[PDB]
Length: 61
Length: 66
Figure 1 (tube, chains in turn brown, blue):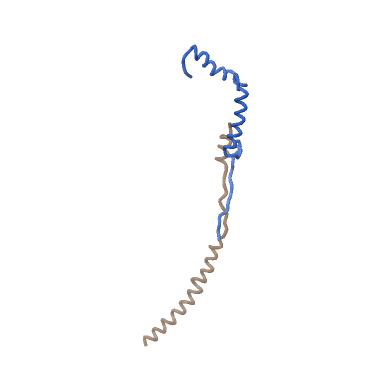
Figure 2 (cartoon, rainbow over the protein chains, first blue to last red):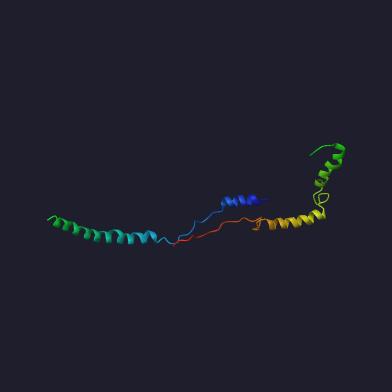
């Protein structure tokens, strides 16, 4: 005896890390690829889109 | 614990005659000791084995990510 008691305080006292990272390039491997996604391809793609719209204006004449 | 007083006088005092000694409780009885040692180890084998007078603290881990 005193095992449970020893264990009691020690278990109630015994604490725990929380499990590591691996692969959290995602937060970043996002936003930069996101600039490619969105902005870089976006803006270019809108630039394309507009010329056809302007030219569909022209084709409306 | 139970009854009849002349018979139980023979036995109920013999409940506690055993208890009315405690280094070999009027007999621990070598056979009791031997088979006890057998079953107490064998019990230990039949148990889980991570010492029973020690605290199994924690472990840590790291899960599959790509």
